Image: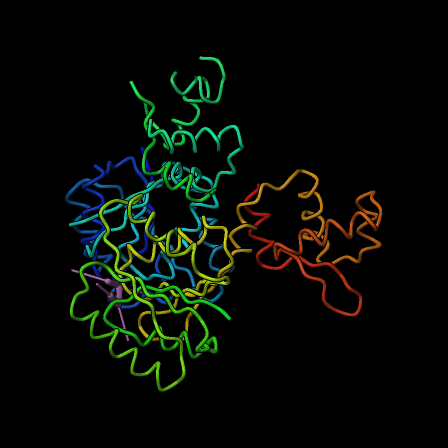
Length: 200
Length: 212
RNA sequence: AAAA
């Protein structure tokens, strides 16, 4: 079970693609935030989405309208919605107004809930990230960790154990949860490259 | 001197509006990131921009072209550009590809640099929100139980002078001043009026709402 | 790539 949290523009097909790609189920939650007032294009897109959801056995959408006047007053409404969504929260920034997508994006990050955000090339190519990515980039690494990463960066991958001079691993599984390295040779991933780049 | 970091689509109007609303100077770094390869509508918007920039003594744009294969690979390239921009970084995410603007936004936050982001209304309207680095750091800060006790009081009294706050919290005014100065750095409270009553602003309300 |  999961939650979809998106805004809606004039084209419901972006959301239909997201719902099928991630195998949406009826038990899931679908929450659509739209600007106030609801313009004709957005309303038509919602009715078009209702008819197509009712055929495909998807979850019924809940629609929230919010005025977009102040960054904090609008974030306040986005946050109240977010605390009512069970994790993980699936989001896609390719559709709807940029202002509202910005508030959704910032809303899930500061809420510290689990999430997966997708962003597409126009509506073919696609990139994604999650709460683990953001937390791995926002983390203040200690020097025991930082100089271990810098060694892995310079050695490119127990030969490691006789460099920092320790025993022979509990920290390895801890850093594998942050997705910054893998594991035989301990291999640093691209996310770890960004880690080191942020703290050099 | 400031710096501007934006991406470009087919329309330069929002960038020229940004430059006009923030009083852009010729000594500023204007940096534009575009996808690779540069398509013809983006080449045309960039030529339309340079003509108007020269006539208004705006900064000349330095243009970088980025490939976007993977999230981490593309962010890596955005960070290289960000980490050579002088602070503060002024950005406007209402233009160009959404993928690039997401990386620009995410790149700026994690670079811990100073910034102001604008996001406008596509339909041309006057609706516009903005935020800055203190905004994000405020919402993500780990607030101690003691710090939360102080914020909870300002919400229930709606403004209280330093002397009464020190009484309500069983602390010295000397130590309350230092703590109020530290919270003021994050932008979550202000102290206006001739009575110097400490008050929670809208940002402080969101901070309190996150810890319930 | 201005509710794509």
